[PDB]
Image (cartoon, rainbow over all chains, first blue to last red; front, top):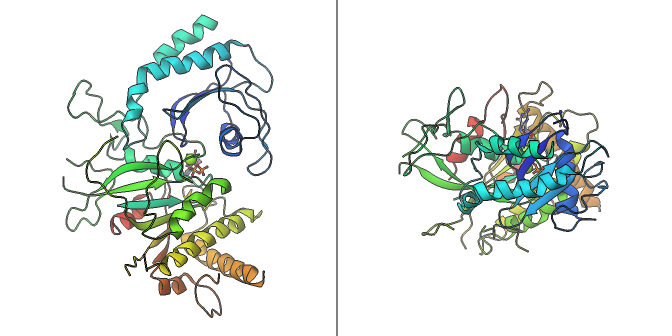
Length: 135
Length: 270
Ligand SMILES: Nc1nc2c(ncn2[C@@H]2O[C@H](COP(=O)(O)OP(=O)(O)OP(=O)(O)O)[C@@H](O)[C@H]2O)c(=O)[nH]1
Ligand SMILES: [Mg+2]
């Protein structure tokens, strides 16, 4: 516990799944995708990798940017939230594999084209099981 | 059967989209209409909230939506389930970031030729039957709570975007050649309306005209959106170009006018 909020949001912005422990300013993540995906100054698609950036002022100040995963086929992004350079590497282990669970369980659903609705409601159970294994 | 959602980031563009889809999915009391699990053929996905958390859209998303108009009903609400007996249309949310606005406008500017088909899984430059992507309406969504701020950057940059948006459609009218002109009615929607600072629609209409018109003057010194000769720019001038411009309020979240007024505008226009 006590490492803030985890979010699972689509390329187009909708948040499929959210877990929030501390109140996190929306703009934090909002600033994050703005630079990583829209302006793109210092990022390369990968798993468990670099997760660093500073946005400049096309869209605001930005902090420096958690650790994150991208699934191009499904267009979902996985953000686990640091506390400004506090940490414990488990989230890395957490965030990439945790896409592997989420993808596994709901990968089929992104195929349906008409809607932004992926119902992943039972997920939280799995999530807890995972959180403990890293303690 | 397409209506374009347009506006700057934070407008609640992507979130309004979410609101309309989950409408039929939960009864009043925000109940999941489908938690009687294990109905293979028909069961609608369970939804936990009438609108979901969102962050800034990095891509257009086109979403499936049906408008009910039971007779005398006008467009019925977006929260009534249907199972058909409905006009069907595509609501396409779009990115608001200034970098991502441009592609959308290219669509606005070329009339029929482009049409309005987005190559999903990305931007350009899984269920198949005779479907179309006609463009009959465009919605411009703004934050009427942020508009209140004295920083006044929002109205200026927001009105500027609207200026292009309205301007492109104007160029679209001059593109009737591609002999088959279509009138594009535009809804200017003042969102974030449960917030106390939310600027009233009438004011948003009035401010925009003032901001837009000045921009033309600002740009003219540097085409002339609206009338060839305008003492001042009104939305009413845009009619000349077959553009029904309407300022209407609403809120995606919280207590307020609701989104139905918008929704009623949309159904009347497909
Ligand atoms: N209180 C309140 N919040 C709203 C309203 N409409 C939208 N929001 C919130 O505004 C936040 C940002 O809006 P989004 O829809 O996610 O962003 P966007 O409008 O798609 O704009 P982009 O950044 O270009 O993608 C969301 O968290 C919404 O919950 C509203 O009417 N009232
Ligand atoms: Mg969005």
